[PDB]
Image 1 (cartoon, rainbow, N blue to C red):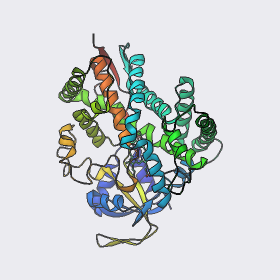
Image 2 (tube, helix red, strand yellow; image 1 turned 180 degrees about the vertical axis):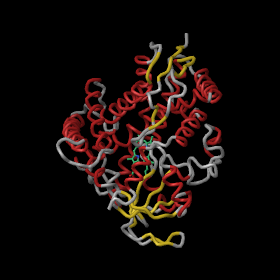
Image 3 (cartoon, rainbow, N blue to C red; image 1 turned 90 degrees about the vertical axis):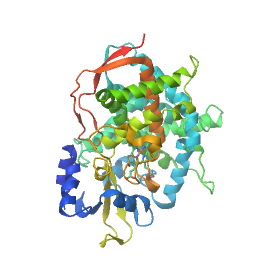
Image 4 (cartoon, rainbow, N blue to C red; image 1 turned 45 degrees about the vertical axis):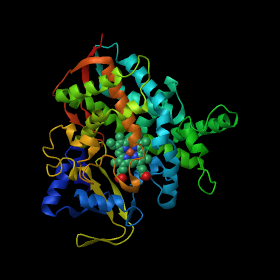
Length: 439
Ligand code: HEM
């Protein structure tokens, strides 16, 4: 049955959503009943509800994706697998996204961001930030996932992913003239492309032309579980498809918005500049940014977090009750759906005083003063974001090189709105800015 799916969809595109939950909390409370995407759903608002859903994976709940997302991502990815297979895939992914592993890719990421800024920003009087950020974010994935530096090949894959992403928000009608149908065709083309990259990679590894750690493709190809089993081609394809979905639209949001919010709060921009320039003062010219420099960008990371609080790229996500669960006096029946949202804590004065104000100081001392399960841009528990530290690296390096290159900037439209009907919140006009390069 339609249930409340239509009203929820209406509120989502309306870019409100907070109200959708607010009025249901006002009428029923934090733990209330609803029907979404044809399933009986219970929304658990607030920190206590967040802990229930997020911290009890495989105990009381399991990740549940809607049918259409399963068809576009595949059934063999880390996001669509459960139980033991999920834990193995996270272990394989940790070989690239883990803190020790991520440090070996900072050089490649730094170089691309540096080259992108110099080529497409440094010499312009004005730029439209959003398309540049999208290009940079995708190209970093192409380099770090597949070692693809060829610009035409990067653009080809970039266009293909855009077509697939259209279907994830269209009506799931697999018919010749619908958006979902074209997305499914795009996924088929991408699968064939990635299959050829897998084959050539297997050869390149056997002939000593590629290493086991150079990129994500090699890490996943060389992974073996505790019993010596490698991942299958379908598992590698679906994981790459899922990782492209997860990485492109999400990271684009804070990167595109960070300098919009900073332009409205110049005192915070002043502190970002001072932090970044102080880091450069202690380096010789030509010396590359290091992982140690990265960890010194504390205030910059506080600005990024406050951007994520006010404009979460992922409003929330769904689980399925794998057992009858007793919560707040009620019993969520097995087979029912559960939903948590950042909108129950992120915009609330109760958890973040003056929530409408941009205050990076909320995350002072590495977030010491943030209450548990109130700031959740990357979720939590066994299903927490695989790539959050990858995103953090991109944002910090991007901010660093921008501040290094430019003395100042000025928004062309200071009153530009920040909407997103599709999940990703972004500058409504792409955030055009005038640029002032350092002399
Ligand atoms: C850029 C690289 C990124 C990669 C490779 C990535 C990858 C992933 C993957 C594979 C998962 C599923 C983990 C699992 O099922 O075990 C996940 C979860 C998640 N991601 Fe990310 N992600 C990235 C960036 C981001 C960003 C920037 C945000 C938001 C600021 C974000 C928000 C989330 C959230 C909230 C979840 C958990 C959803 C839930 O538990 O219901 N991701 N990510």
